[PDB]
Image: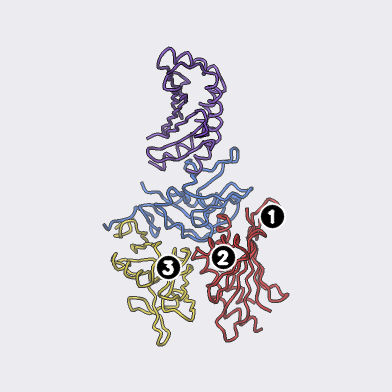
Chain colours: A purple, B red, C blue, D yellow
Amino acid sequence: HSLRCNLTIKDPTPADPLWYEAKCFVGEILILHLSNIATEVKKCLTQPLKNLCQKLRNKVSNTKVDTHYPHLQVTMIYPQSQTPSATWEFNISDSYFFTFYTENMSWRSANDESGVIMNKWKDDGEFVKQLKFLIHECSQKMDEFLKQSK
Amino acid sequence: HSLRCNLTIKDPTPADPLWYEAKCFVGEILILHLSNINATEVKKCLTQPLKNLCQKLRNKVSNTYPHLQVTMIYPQSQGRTPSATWEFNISDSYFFTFYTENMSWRSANDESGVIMNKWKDDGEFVKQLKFLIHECSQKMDEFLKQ
Amino acid sequence: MEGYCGPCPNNWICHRNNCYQFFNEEKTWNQSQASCLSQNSSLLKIYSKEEQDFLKLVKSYHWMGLVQIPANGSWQWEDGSSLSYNQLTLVEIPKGSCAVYGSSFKAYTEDCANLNTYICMKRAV
Amino acid sequence: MEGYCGPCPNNWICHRNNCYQFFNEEKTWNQSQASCLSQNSSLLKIYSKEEQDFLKLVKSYHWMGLVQIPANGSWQWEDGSSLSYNQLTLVEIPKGSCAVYGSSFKAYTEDCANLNTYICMKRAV
């Protein structure tokens, strides 16, 4: 399989003060688990993912929603390079869906309402750079690790 | 007095590339000096075993930065089975001792005891401390007689 | 179960069709590499702790095929593949762009101009 | 077989058609001998320093096939052949009728009931 990181951004509550969680898998094996509450790849990914979760929180704070438990889920999918590329899938509250492909810096929305939010988000040059840059920064170590799994 | 070997294991630097040094004394007389930079029978007996031990200690320290000092003390056996004391000092912080005679240990405190317990799980390491004594006991005795 | 290990040069140590030889002549890293090359091999590479388990027992220090690129501080094998922390633990000493194998899947950085014994290896094909 | 070493059990180390395996399980001398026997081999014997040269580099301590006759203190191999001074140097510790291999063609006498790693060997035929 690929290396997959599932990020969740949500509102903390007295019952659960978690506002972000990150779980990176290779197949069934959990390889990294982060929250506000494999060594070399864990090391490479940790701060960039934490930094990205902070940025995503800010993006969520500025997004106009309309649904009848707000939450952002982001899935990063990195295949073994064998030029390194990834897919970033965004799901805002099970309502808006769009995808960024780092390979050609291209985007796809599920519908026009998702496209409006997507277009606002991708206007943020820093945000888009973080998505592309994380891949280049950790590509080699991700490849190396995926080699171990074989 | 006894035969004493003082070992130092440290990180090399540009100012000093030495990572190990071994100095064996009998009283004031220096009788063996080894290092990675650059009495005959006892020097011959001790040399490779000490080098081999320093290489092991380097690996142990790497899995524990830290500076290590080791003192071996070997008294003349007389009619007794040959024995020695091995004293360990990790970074002036953790201290423990091994006694080869009955293969027993003593730590200065519980924090030292934790590291000591980890180190003595290494069967090779413990054998090296004991075996060095039996390998060179006779020649050490012979020399101390002189 | 019982099969054959090779092909290897005469008198070399064979395991899983990998061929090893342990050379006792003291040479610089560069001279050690040239010696291995002249025998259709390269310096020791650790590709798998599991598959090369017995090498944990090799005492002393020996030149192996691990080299630094000082520009970015990265380490690679002669063949261009990257050093993996799952292969080997590298103990870095500020000065030195070569490394000796030092038992137990540990390596120590050393000045490439130092004289060491060395280990050649031909990987199974 | 030209350029090849064997036949040996799967994953064993081969040199001059001698087969070696380095077992990491800790066993008594007797349990170590039984393990080697069950795999059609015996505990390590040093028959030739020249032909088994690489074994000088094997660190740590491992049960080998060297046993004492306490009646007059003599040592021999499992196969009944005598210990020869040119095969290895035996470091005798007053109590113990078995021996561990300890690198550099040295062996150390050891209580047979002690747990050690062990080395099995099948001699070339």
Q: CA distance from mark 1 to mark 2?
A: 21 Å
- Could you say where residue C121 lies in the image, as x and y percent from the top left? 44, 52
Mark 3 or 2: the one toward you: 3
Question: Which residue does the numbered mark 1 point to in the structure image?
Answer: B16
Q: Amino acid at mark 1?
A: Asp
The numbered dot on residue B130 is none
Q: Amino acid at mark 3?
A: Asn
Question: Which residue does the numbered mark 2 point to in the structure image?
Answer: B53
Q: Amino acid at mark 2?
A: Leu
Q: CA distance from mark 3 to mark 2?
A: 19 Å
Going from the N terminus, do you reach mark 1 or mark 2 first?
1
**Mark 3 packing: few (<14 Cα in 10 Å), some, or many (20+)?**
many
Q: Chain of mark 1?
A: B
Figure quadrant of the N terminus of chain A? top left
**Front-lying residue, A96 or D8:** A96
Relative side of C106 to D79, left or right: right
Residue occupying the point 35% across, 52% down? C17
Question: SS of the residue at dot 2?
Answer: helix
In the figure, residue B50 lies in which quadrant? bottom right
Question: Is residue C37 shown to the viewer in this render?
Answer: no
Discs 3, 2 touching: Cβ within 8 Å? no
Q: Chain of mark 2?
A: B
Q: Chain of mark 3?
A: D
Q: CA distance from mark 1 to mark 3?
A: 39 Å
| Callout count | 3
The numbered dot on residue D116 is 3
Question: SS of the residue at dot 1?
Answer: loop
Figure quadrant of the C terminus of chain A? top left
- Could you say where residue A27 lies in the image, as x and y percent from the top left? 38, 37
Question: Is residue A37 shown to the viewer in this render?
Answer: yes
- Could you say where residue C62 lies in the image, as x and y percent from the top left? 52, 56
